[PDB]
Image 1 (tube, protein in one colour):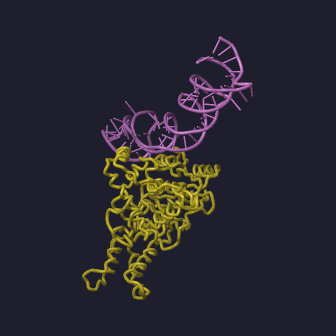
Image 2 (cartoon, chains in turn red, cyan; image 1 turned 90 degrees about the horizontal axis):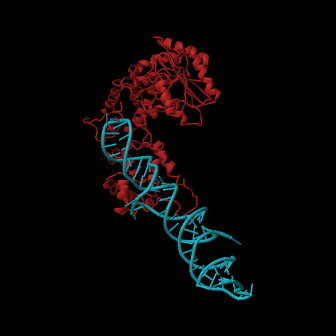
Image 3 (spheres, helix red, strand yellow; image 1 turned 45 degrees about the vertical axis):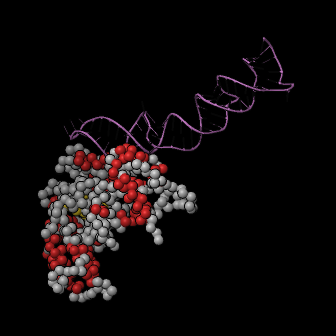
Amino acid sequence: FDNLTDRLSRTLRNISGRGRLTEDNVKDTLREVRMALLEADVALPVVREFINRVKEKAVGHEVNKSLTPGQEFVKIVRNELVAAMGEENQTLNLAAQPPAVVLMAGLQGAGKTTSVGKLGKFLREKHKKKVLVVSADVYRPAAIKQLETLAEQVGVDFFPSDVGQKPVDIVNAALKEAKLKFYDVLLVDTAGRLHVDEAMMDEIKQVHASINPVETLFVVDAMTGQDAANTAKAFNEALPLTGVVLTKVDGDARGGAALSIRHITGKPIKFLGVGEKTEALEPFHPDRIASRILGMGDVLSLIEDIESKVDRAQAEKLASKLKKGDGFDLNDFLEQLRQMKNMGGMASLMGKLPGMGQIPDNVKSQMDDKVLVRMEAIINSMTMKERAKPEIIKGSRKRRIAAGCGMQVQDVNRLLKQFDDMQRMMKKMK
RNA sequence: UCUGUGCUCUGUGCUCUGUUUACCAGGUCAGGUCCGAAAGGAAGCAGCCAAGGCAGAGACGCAGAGCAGGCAGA
């Protein structure tokens, strides 16, 4: 699909194709996009519908004047992409009360356990709250184990029972535990050996109605895709509050149909998480995905951080002395850094997004990030004062930083200006 | 002249306190770097610590000098 999200700007071409008509720009794209889908799993029965509705509109509308059609088209395209997928209902993944019951019903494994992590993981790096997890699966091996890891490796205990093949108890057991300790949120992955899905649920049956869980979720890898539909489906009935997510994004190639099918049941998602890494999990809201043409955008996010910074120096001392008396030192510069990789200086989103308003070049984003660490290299390879008078960088005083930071000269001189010029231009206020 | 008396001045030794110090043989060395397939190692800037610089104080140490009722002994 991704490479369709290009058809996007591939479309932002006044030139147009051969057809004098350029009239076809659309339909192609349609089909084009239309293609990229099913090819990427995606069911089709539906499609007709979309592709249709799409059409429908046309012969019943026009872009309010004062606005190039081409564009409009989209709003519409986009428009229906939404509906096409998780139409619109903003999933409510946060606290109804506290603490909580995360019944994690999983078909055969696959994200089975994993998932939980970032999930939990996620919420700890969110509310003073107290997670808590439990190995709610005894058929397949590495219950705790593989999982167990993270648990600590994230600063989040968990609990289970070696070997010990029997949910319920253990579950129950767990539960009240944290509870007794009065934690805030529990996550507990489960499943069963029944070769039939009704048997799966059949299991969750007791599982559920024995515990009395508030929030319940199933999950699946796009591996299965549109097929999945059913699976989940049968259950939306079991429990409508039944919301879910799709294991592995970067973990397939089919996707679509997966999430597609879902939707088309009134299905309820909340996240998705590209795959590996303790954080790849993400919230979810059609648009969000799709954001940026067919799915993920931010920065708006990464964007909004400016506000974080820009308006925080405000935050040394906002004044912390109304004025001007010279009260701080310009090494933010490097200050920027930290934040950022400390937390969120991950690529912030710096992608750039649509080259807009001016499309400039490939290395600009494209070529420093991955590697805007370097700049850092030094800095900490220098006294405070240094960065306050970034104009006392004699060949002498620095080569040491050069080596002291481990970087053969060049790199530096070859930067010193990306500092004294930044401003230069930067500082160009009338 | 020496010594005591104490007091003062000056130098300094030690201590306490404040402050100050990119690199130019201290310690610990984040980050980054280097060697190694790894196991493991190494050099090392910033910071901090030590140390140095500048000061105040010690009716604190060690000294030189001066001291109406300066006063004493030799």
